[PDB]
Every structure is written in C-alpha cells, then in structure tokens.
Amino acid sequence: ACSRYEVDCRGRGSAC
Amino acid sequence: IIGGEFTTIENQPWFAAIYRRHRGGSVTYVCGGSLISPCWVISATHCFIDYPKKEDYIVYLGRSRLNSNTQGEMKFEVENLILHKDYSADTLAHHNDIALLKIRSKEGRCAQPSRTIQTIALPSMYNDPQFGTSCEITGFGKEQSTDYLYPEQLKMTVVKLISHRECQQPHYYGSEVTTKMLCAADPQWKTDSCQGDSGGPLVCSLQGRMTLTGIVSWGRGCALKDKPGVYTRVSHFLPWIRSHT
Ligand SMILES: *Cc1cc(C*)cc(C*)c1
C-alpha cells in the first residue's frame, strides 16, 4: 500500500 | 503514453480521469477509465485494490488536463466501486483486471453527452477485431519509462492487435497471457501505454462502431521490443459487466 500519492502504483513501471 | 500525440478530450470523449482524495495531502491522479453508459465508468481493479473505499475517489469526464480544469469538464462522486472478486497479480500479469464505478454528481445526476463527453459501445459477446487491426489508446501516463512527471495534456497513440498465438510465443509473454487478455503494440515498438495509463481504453472500429475492446492492464516496461501492452479483453466479460450493472 506504501504511504503514497503515487500515480497508478501497480501499472507497467513501477515497483508493484 | 509513449510516443503518439497530444490530443484533446473531444477526440476521446468517453475517457474518464480518476483521482483519489487525501488523507493527505489533497488530490492526486489514480488511473484512466471509460464511460460505457451515463452512470457507469469501467477501469482496472489493480488501480483501486490498495484503497478500495469509494469515498476516496473522484471521476472527471470531459477533462483534457491532468492538474488543471478544462472548460466542459464535469465532476462525479463514486456511488459504487466494484472490483473483480477474482483479481490476481503474478510477477507482472494481472488477471481479472476490471473494475466498475457507478458515478453520480452532487446534484445527483449521471453524465450528459456533450461535445466533450460521449459513451463508448461495448463489443458483443466474444466479438474482437482481427489481429493486425489498428486501435487507439489514450491516457495521462508517462511519456517515457524513466520520467518521474506525467504529461499535463491528454495523449493518444495507435497500436495494432497481435494474435494470441504470437503474444503467447515465449519470445513475447508466453504463458502469462490468457484468453481473458488481448495484446496490442507498435510494429516498430516505439509507441505504447505506460504507468498512469492503466484503466484507460483500447478502442477499435469493430463492425460499424468505435468499441471498447480492451482496458489498459499490464506489460513488461513500456515500448520495449517483443513486450506488448496487455489489455483486459472486454468481450469476454459481458456477463460480469451485465450482472454488476
Ligand atoms: C509503494 C507501493 C504502492 C502501491 C499502491 C502498491 C505497491 C505494490 C507498492
């Protein structure tokens, strides 16, 4: 879940 | 979107821009979606699986900019947030990556079509275009894999459907892709969807009509050789969509 204001955190990318 | 061109919402009027409230920290973009009826936006479960509370989310329609208001935009609350009970992510693949948002304005109305807002048709059961067919994808995703900032203006590009046979070459994705997915990419590997584009439309002409054939879902990197974008295959989810809608 992190803490984040991260855009599309499970998109092609991207840590998750 | 890697490559392609800056566009405006009039050219992709079914595009929905989904944001989350903070918390926080005010408001940040989450993912794209598509308007499939006046009250319903379809997107990808992975966009929401970490924070599944409908109260966190805002949906804009008719909006062409990421962090600035566009004339003709309309703002919505999320009355229902519906995630796929069978969502799973392995290493890179997301299966059942499909989500429904019931929208409602504070007033409390659904969407009105206008020059910036139109619904997009769904395909008929199991109807997909032929491989090699040119489709469009659109979104506020990264313009390069390595960027840390997102484009402020909406982008679209054109990619081509790839046969399952071909996408499930090991040389491509192998077993990671299922009959519940479609692959689409640039013949020269220079344009693609990227982070931030998830949940957005893969739109094709299919027997008369502009159709929502896929939802942007996953891929290895963005715009890499033999690594197409993978989309959730809408035509294989009609019953899911009918029951929950
Ligand atoms: C840091 C982070 C954030 C999200 C939304 C998801 C994962 C897996 C990691």
Image (cartoon, coloured by chain):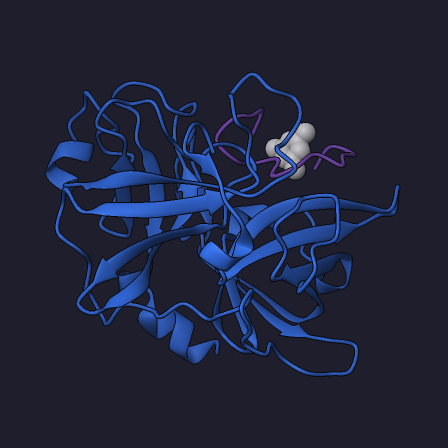
Above or below, B208 against B176 in this view is: below
Q: Is residue B142 left or right of residue B203?
A: right
Q: The purple chain is which one?
A: A
Q: Quadrant of residue B131?
A: top left
List x then y, in percent, for residue B90.
42, 35
The answer, for residue B12, to whether it is visible in the render is: no
Residue at x 29% of width, y 23% of height = B189
Q: Which one is in front, B89 or B235?
A: B235
Residue at x 34% of width, y 22% of height = B190
Above or below, B206 against B177 in this view is: below
Residue at x 55% of width, y 50% of height = B32
Q: Which one is in front, B78 or B203?
A: B203
Q: Is residue B175 left or right of residue B117?
A: left
Q: Which one is in front, B104 or B1?
A: B1
List x then y, in percent, for residue B117.
54, 68
Count of number-bearing discs: 0
Chain B shade: blue
List x then y, in percent, for residue B212.
35, 60
